[PDB]
Every structure is written in C-alpha cells, then in structure tokens.
Image (cartoon, coloured by chain):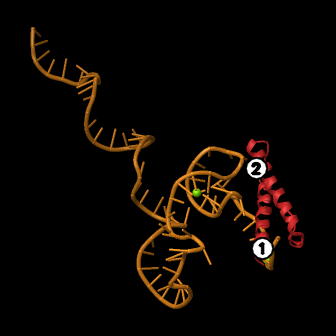
Amino acid sequence: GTTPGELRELTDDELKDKLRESKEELFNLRFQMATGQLSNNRRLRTVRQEIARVYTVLRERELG
RNA sequence: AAGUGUUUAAGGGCGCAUGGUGGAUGCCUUGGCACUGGGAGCCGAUGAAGGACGUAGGAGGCUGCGAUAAGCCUCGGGG
Ligand SMILES: [Mg+2]
Ligand SMILES: [Mg+2]
C-alpha cells in the first residue's frame, strides 16, 4: 500500500493512526464483500499487508 | 391291372461372408524394484510427528495456507 521508505521514516503516532484506520478498513471491506456488494480480493490482501507489516514494525522498534 | 420313381424343412448340423458382446494380444509411460557416488542423518514446551475445522467471486476433492487463512514483508536472480 505504502512504501517502506516512508513507513520506516514515519513515527509512532502515525503508525498507530494507520493501524487503527487499517483495522477499520479491514472491518469495512471484509463486510461489504460479506454482504455481497464487493467483488475483488486484492483489497483485503493489501490491508492484510499493512496490518502485518505495522505489527512487525511495532514489535521491531519495541525490542530495538 | 400292375409295380417302378425325385418332389416339402417346423427345425437341426456343417462350412462360407458379414456382424454383435469380451478386452488378451502389439506398441507406450507421469509409475515400482535393485544398486553407485555424495549430503543430511534427527524433529519438539520459543509447543513436534499426524489430524479436525476453516480459508478461493463461484457447489465439492487434491495441494498451499491459517480469522493476517491458494498467503505477507525485507533482500537479491527473471521478464
Ligand atoms: Mg486441504
Ligand atoms: Mg533479487
């Protein structure tokens, strides 16, 4: 979704913000496709991408 | 008057020519068997071997995967 060049140089409050918005987008998109109004898959995949990498970066900077 | 004498096939048998089931035979392998030369010779509470369930816009099965569910990141080969 967004480049690691920006992602690694951006800060704690902002990855918290994209964390909450990405959970919110997972919520919305998964359940419009659940309702049956949505068509394609790559949206859930890329929001999955975002949540996975933000959680990884969270624990990375927590440990380091 | 007289005696002499083939003449039919319900079916059947035998050959001939055509067919019908049944898939041996000939030719093949994506499969198995037995060895040679090397590598690794263990896997698990930082949770194994094997499973259940789920996961695809689609109804099931194989395979991959695990509410982040036929996958994701960073790194490099390829078009
Ligand atoms: Mg399966
Ligand atoms: Mg590369």
Residue under numbered circle 1: A62
Please name the color used to draw chain B. Answer: orange
Circle 1: residue type: Glu
Say which of A26 and B40 sits in front.
A26
Tag on residue A24? none
Say which of B62 and B43 sits in front.
B43
Where on the picture, by quarter, is residue A4?
Answer: bottom right
- Which SS class for mark 1? helix
Relative image position of residue B36 (x, y in whole percent): 48, 89
Q: Is residue B53 left or right of residue A28?
A: left
Pointers 2 and 1 in contact (C-beta within 8 Å)? no
Mark 1 chain:
A
Which residue shows up at 88% across the image and 64% down it?
A: A14
Residue under numbered circle 2: A30
Relative image position of residue B50 (x, y in whole percent): 49, 64
Alpha carbons under labels 2 and 1: distance apart: 30 Å
The quadrant of the picture occupied by the N terminus of chain A is bottom right
Mark 2 chain:
A
- Which SS class for mark 2? helix
Circle 2: residue type: Arg
